[PDB]
Image (tube, coloured by chain):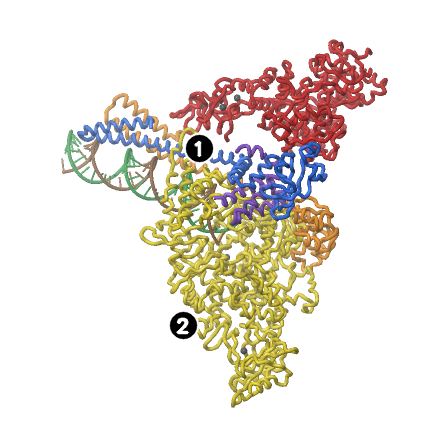
Chain colours: A orange, B blue, C yellow, D purple, E red, F green, G brown
Amino acid sequence: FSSLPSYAAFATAQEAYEQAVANGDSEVVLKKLKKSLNVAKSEFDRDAAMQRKLEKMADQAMTQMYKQARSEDKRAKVTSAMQTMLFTMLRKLDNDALNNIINNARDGCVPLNIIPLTTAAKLMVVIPDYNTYKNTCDGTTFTYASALWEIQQVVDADSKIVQLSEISMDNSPNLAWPLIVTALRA
Amino acid sequence: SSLPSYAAFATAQEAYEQAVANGDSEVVLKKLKKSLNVAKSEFDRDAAMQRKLEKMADQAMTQMYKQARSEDKRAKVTSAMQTMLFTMLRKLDNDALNNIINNARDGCVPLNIIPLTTAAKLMVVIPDYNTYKNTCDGTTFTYASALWEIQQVVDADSKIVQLSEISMDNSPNLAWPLIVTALRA
Amino acid sequence: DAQSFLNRVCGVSAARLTPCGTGTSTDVVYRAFDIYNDKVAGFAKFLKTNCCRFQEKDEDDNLIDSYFVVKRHTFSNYQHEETIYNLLKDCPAVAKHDFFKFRIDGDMVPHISRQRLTKYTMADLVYALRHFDEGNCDTLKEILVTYNCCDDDYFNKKDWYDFVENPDILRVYANLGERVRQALLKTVQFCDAMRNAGIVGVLTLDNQDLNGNWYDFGDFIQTTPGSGVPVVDSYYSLLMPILTLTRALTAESHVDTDLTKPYIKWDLLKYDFTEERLKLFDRYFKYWDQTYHPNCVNCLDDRCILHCANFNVLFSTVFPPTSFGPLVRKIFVDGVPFVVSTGYHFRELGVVHNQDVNLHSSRLSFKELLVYAADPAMHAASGNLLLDKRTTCFSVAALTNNVAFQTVKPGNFNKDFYDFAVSKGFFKEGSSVELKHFFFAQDGNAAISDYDYYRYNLPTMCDIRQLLFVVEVVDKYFDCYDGGCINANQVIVNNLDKSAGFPFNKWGKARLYYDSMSYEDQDALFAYTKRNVIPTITQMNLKYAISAKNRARTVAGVSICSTMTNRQFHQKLLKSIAATRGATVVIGTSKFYGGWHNMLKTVYSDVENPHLMGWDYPKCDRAMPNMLRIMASLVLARKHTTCCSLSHRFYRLANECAQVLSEMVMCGGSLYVKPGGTSSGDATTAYANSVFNICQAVTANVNALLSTDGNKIADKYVRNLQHRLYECLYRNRDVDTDFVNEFYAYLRKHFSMMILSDDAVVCFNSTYASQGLVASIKNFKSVLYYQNNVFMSEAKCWTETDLTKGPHEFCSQHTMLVKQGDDYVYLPYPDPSRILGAGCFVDDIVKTDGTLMIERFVSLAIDAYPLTKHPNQEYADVFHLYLQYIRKLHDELTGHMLDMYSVMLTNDNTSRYWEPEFYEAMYTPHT
Amino acid sequence: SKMSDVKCTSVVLLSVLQQLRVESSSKLWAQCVQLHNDILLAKDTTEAFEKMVSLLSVLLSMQGAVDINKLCEEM
Amino acid sequence: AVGACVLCNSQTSLRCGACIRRPFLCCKCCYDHVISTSHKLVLSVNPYVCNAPGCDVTDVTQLYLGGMSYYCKSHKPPISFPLCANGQVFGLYKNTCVGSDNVTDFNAIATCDWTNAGDYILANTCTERLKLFAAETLKATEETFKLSYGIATVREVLSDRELHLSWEVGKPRPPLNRNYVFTGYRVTKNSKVQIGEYTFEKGDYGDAVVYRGTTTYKLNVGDYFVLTSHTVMPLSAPTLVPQEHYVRITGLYPTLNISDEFSSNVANYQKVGMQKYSTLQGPPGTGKSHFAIGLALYYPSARIVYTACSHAAVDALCEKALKYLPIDKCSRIIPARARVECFDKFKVNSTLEQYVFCTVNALPETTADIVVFDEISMATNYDLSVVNARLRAKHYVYIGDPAQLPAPRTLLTKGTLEPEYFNSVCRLMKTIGPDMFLGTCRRCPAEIVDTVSALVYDNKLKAHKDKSAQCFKMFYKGVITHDVSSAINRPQIGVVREFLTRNPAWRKAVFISPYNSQNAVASKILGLPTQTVDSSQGSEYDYVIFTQTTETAHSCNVNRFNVAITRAKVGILCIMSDRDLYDKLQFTSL
RNA sequence: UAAUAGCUUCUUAGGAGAAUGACGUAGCAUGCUACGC
RNA sequence: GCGUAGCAUGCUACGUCAUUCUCCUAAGAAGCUA
Ligand SMILES: [Mg+2]
Ligand SMILES: [Mg+2]
Ligand SMILES: [Zn+2]
Ligand SMILES: [Zn+2]
Ligand SMILES: [Zn+2]
Ligand SMILES: [Zn+2]
Ligand SMILES: [Zn+2]
């Protein structure tokens, strides 16, 4: 706008017009100078609108570039998080039993629903009432999934540890069922 | 509007009005008309920006008020909720609610949920003999607008105390606060 | 004499008989023939009058379940049936016939005597279960009692027939499983005997008594021996819904198929039961002449996926439930051993293997990382074994080391609005407008006790011959839309600040994944799902919303890996449905600016004697059978006749099943297996539900038309239509487009319908529905009973005989006819309790301020405007209460703003929100 | 207007109990939720008042969580 | 974000930018504050700077409000509006603010640097809000004074136990002791992150430190240390709760013949039960910390929280409770860092117990039935405000004596503070007198109480004991060695060593010295249990050694010497330097 | 922790179009006046 | 009669601004329904 020579042309035309008006020149010269100033300011406004459009387009392009940069930086963060999760879950795997069962497969393909059932080293049992507790995992060891599990901890709905001696028919109302008994394979 | 552009527009309008009041003819009239129009255009350009500025200011005022009220309401949320609860509880004026609240002000709070089924256990703590005299008469216990039968009274030492051991003179030797276990009647 | 007749009927067999008739005359009974001849067709309850029935009594003179049917007919039929029986005499599955000629009065009337039949036939059981009316169920009760399924006092229970209230009825029915299975075996023996004896004939249910013996040879023609053919299309197909209801094949889990011997211990590693399925099919459905592919990946089209999947539904109940689900395989990436799912074993679609399995890789692109972190193979393989005794559903693994118990908070009380309301005369004792909608709270056992409701989803084998025609009628209903695959750049997502499912919600909303993945690797993922199966976990989120009943509501958040591809696959069709006006499926039709009136006028499309009807689906999203969900997915996929190949469409269907129909469900930190039923969070949920609703309605019409007598249908066009409908169902294997069009036009003329995914208003013809030529409420009850395993109590189903009052309820909006301008229009008005409850109870503390939320009350008043024209003043006062509260809120907002500054707002257009005209303009058809 | 006044005070009371972290005590929170739901789904005023008494006894049982004197001396 | 004016509690959005705490101020009060002092920068929701493309003007009365921004005199738009005008300063809630005359002391509180004693005496005689703000900004000043210290670095590691020290050139070297901790840095290329929390303390030989750290990382030459700045948390509770008198005992229940030992304090127990809060004044060794435990035994059903600003005081209280109170119902809450070796004999960190012991700064937000604040003399208004904020209780009781040594107040370097202005409760003890008082020495030998009853106190304290002749006054010059900004007197330590083997019964004597440097460095030379006088407050010992390191105004303080000598129980050796202090007491000849 | 879809209300920003008003430039039609032929 | 010039009236094209309306997109808040 101001940097362009159109503004300089407008300024010099206005200065000439003011000097002529203060000098009281002839009316025809006044009209000629008014026409010159009009075309000068016409070119000025013609050039200015392009500047406004150009600066708005540059601003929206800068906003778009910032948005894309932020999205690209978020993609890398989510990729790193997913990789760390996948490799941590991999490292948590029980390699010996998993390899045994997968090799025993005829085609190398096994259903997912038997991977925990035959290779998990920890069992969590959620028990809603006392009769269920008596029937499924009474005592300190019990049988499930064709294995032998031993109790290592019993916690209630509050995740507050419960001793095995507190789980009685008369003390049942004083417990926060369900109890999440965590067992380990023997 | 008290704007210099408005002043120029006003003086052009006044000059044109005076001229047209004279209004002989015709070129001076047209020239003053064009002067009025060109001044009006400049004043209107100024006014448009004023209106846009006012709209932005109103948006700012509205957003700031919403944020301030929201943060204030998310801050005072516990005291406000408790005050509202007790105001509404006072408004109900139920005989049982008033009884239990007045008792809890004096320290005669229950130890577990007041049970509804008949012949169910209620345990309350009685802090002073004055509370025992008001609420307990004989073997009946007047609490929560119902009559309760006292099963066993214990002290802070978990020692059973007989109902004949409670009196105005023997109580100073007793270990207050008591704990009264009763069944609904 | 009538005694010589009894002596002759006794015959050489030492049988002691007591005549059920009266004086050597035919006994009249009301049986349930499956008949098709030159003048009548259908599976209806007729009145047979050609058989003299004698009942045999055992020792101590107790009447037993054995009858001597002594059918008499012409002499030529006598000779013909005697010859056909002589051919089939030695087959063990044939009731011992007795052909003699007894002088009834003065002439030799020839009788054939069937010896030791049961009272009812197989058709009576099939009809009593497929046409269940709890007010008149006397053959079902007698069949259940006479075969020791119950004790004749079991029916003194209030609702002994309800599946969702009395789940012991499943055991009571399953006590008939062995008898039904023995009937199937006897049918196969009889088919083999017909084949070897050179006898051509049709096998119908009403000719096999409940023991299994076959006794009707009237219409059997004999051809060259060794080349007879049994026509069993109508025998098996009608019997199909009974095979899973009674669990006829529960004796196949036992070694040597003996109900006393212990279960078969299949090796856990075994997942490919194709040979077992083939052996079962060749043992029970031997002469079912259409080819059966155990693995539906080999199928020919979606008409062959339905049939083979329907069989796989029945055959999957005898295989262990731990052999299904994803098939994992140990792949290596840069030498590190992954365990990933490279297949699937559907209960309906058989074994499906992925085609792009990379055993040795080195880098994982973002697409592959998303796929490997989406499928539950890693999560279940690295999680602790779980045994959740709170639910009967299968539990896979516990991801965390302790179970999460998620609660639901109570609502936040807007005390200012309540005080304002009671200052306006609201909430008085004895008032008609009272609070019924609240924010109900839930304990820690809410999410799991709500997930446990999937136990109402039972394996249902559908009537495949009838279903394969209902599908044609439904696809005719969906013939005005267009669909197909679109590029990732054409997919528009409404709200991207929404949860991404599990496990992706640990790192961002759906916006992060829709931004990170360029269009290229979204197209790559979509084209991956067309050649591979991606299992996916779906969370269960407790819904925090206001309702009138205290049951916990849960919604399933499907993983972004499933949502993106399902959007890209179905969005064109879904946006085509939402932009169509005046169709059957009114989705995308607003109720403002005259939308409700337009919808109601299009429903009354030139019906003759209109009565409005509406029904309810109890446990709609949980009791929906897997077969109907697969059918809905196939119907929505028929628009892909050019964009997708055959294998592409099958793998899209397999992904849909493995991600929505039966996938791993994350409920409180633990992976469970969803038995079936639609999840309420998949991409095409409302539209699939609309397809299922139309399917149920069309099935109800089909059953209503076929179950009518046929001798009572006066209109020669309707009787012919019933005849050709039976022909198109059970006598024609290819599609007949002419009759499909004719039946579609018939339904549109007499059963005009309006569907929004489970809300339906029907404007049927009352005269036809009374005569039985169009579905009524009872037909929907029967269809739901045998095809959803739920009982539809007639308390939630309404009927409106007067159209000046509109539908009783559609989309929870009652309809009233008001004078607007110069004419009468229908306006939808809500339940006032709902609007007041929305005003008083809010789900956020900042919505309790009021002055911050004036648009809330503007929207609520927009919804509550049509109450102004209600005749009940306590209803009309809700709108005025909201208007006055908006005025008060605006006044105190201006006061607070004037305090917080020293200047009032320059521009204030809030003055139009407490004038009734701004809201009256919302129901005027100009826009 | 007494029946509808109870149904709202139960909502406020359960909100207060939830803010006091009664939600962590599963056995007590189950009873509080049951009482709240039965108050909301009530047709008789006496039953609702008895259940409100039981539900408020939960708040009064914890002495130190609420300042009953300060709260009730503001009326 | 809006707030409340500090001295008027009116809604406002104006905060003084120049003030350390930036307190919310109403329009009138902000105008009076900026029109009076040198504070001229005010922070609204947006700061009051001039929003010209280039301009830096902060004086509010120089700026004008034009359009949507605040501009200076030479940049304002053609339509202008003053900010500071009409006796107010523009901000939210302009027409709802009522000012006050408290704008006079607030100016002094804000502007002053707390160096002179007048700031403290004007910060403790103002109202509740001004008392709170003055304490808040004083703690802010103390915390910000740490920003002027220096960054340390390591030269080499000849031995992994004796680390080498090196400070940044041109910055002061903070003293090396337990009070200061240092967190390392690895700013090289290459992990500009912290490497753990370490500490320093001078070694005897050369420049080496036997250091200590939470982790076991080894430092390269590139690693160096940075002192951790500590933020100042806000405070809103009153310094004192309003005292209300009850007609009879409320919330407390007595016992049946509590004990034959505490039966003399029953009237004061009733007095504590009667009032909302009470104050106990008692000279050292008169049973104040023995009164609180007697009250605890007098109210078994009452949940009691014992508190103290320091760690050694609550440790001694825990020891006395272990002696008297049942140990099953006990607790002791420790900060997670646990820099100082605390008292670990009960179930540590169990807030839900009946009798709870915890320092003030680590107090948990919980209730109680009576809280006994011990040794209020060491406590500041920040501490009282914190104890009234975190600990809501049915009864309060403050015990202590004005004559003991006050809180450190490190930046205070000019003049002396009178006892009555240490904190509000002490002023209450001095204005109308304490609520309870008991003057009778019960721990010290007769000789030392007879000598101290004339130094600070004017012949008031009687005792019940006999002068065991174990009181020795040692006279020596004590050459001065100023090593670590705290004076060390090596020859006095040597004379102590040479006069320890001739005292077979003095082998367990504790060494008491006002300067932490000598106290810490004496550990290797004598091996005796060591404890400075400031941390020795409230803890009694049967054998105590005191040495006056240097003749200064800090080491020869009358109150400090009194509180140091009153810890002895059967005998005390004092190495004294000042002739005046030496002559005033009457001990053995030596 | 908080799903898919539909519709509606409100606020803001941008773009396009339309209509009107004003200003300016260029072009065209008509009328009046000066000079030359 | 013509040309050059100036002024006045009218028409068209283009540019600028102001106002109003409509629509299309984007973002944000909210409500209802299945
Ligand atoms: Mg027959
Ligand atoms: Mg003490
Ligand atoms: Zn097939
Ligand atoms: Zn496609
Ligand atoms: Zn200041
Ligand atoms: Zn003020
Ligand atoms: Zn400036």
Residue under the image location 70 percent in, 55 percent down: A136
- Give me the C-alpha separation between circle 2 and circle 1: 75 Å
Q: Which residue is drawn at 42% across and 40% down?
A: C885
**Tag 2–tag 1 contact (CB < 8 Å):** no
Name the spot of residue G4 as percent of width and height, x first: 21, 33
Q: Name the residue under label 1.
A: C896
Residue extending farthest bottom:
C106
Do the residues at pointers 2 and 1 share their chain?
yes
Say if E400 sits above or below D28 in the image.
Answer: above
Write down the chain letter for disc 2. Answer: C
Q: What element carries label 1?
A: helix
**What residue did someone put label 2 on?**
C715
The three-letter amino acid code for the residue at tag 2 is Asp
Q: Is residue E383 visible?
A: no
Disc 2, SS: loop
Quadrant position of the N terminus of chain C in the picture: bottom right
Foreground of the two, E430 or E455: E430
In the image, is C789 to the left or to the right of E319? left
Compared across the picture, whether A48 is left or right of C378 comes to left
Query: x, y (%) of residue C279?
Result: 64, 69
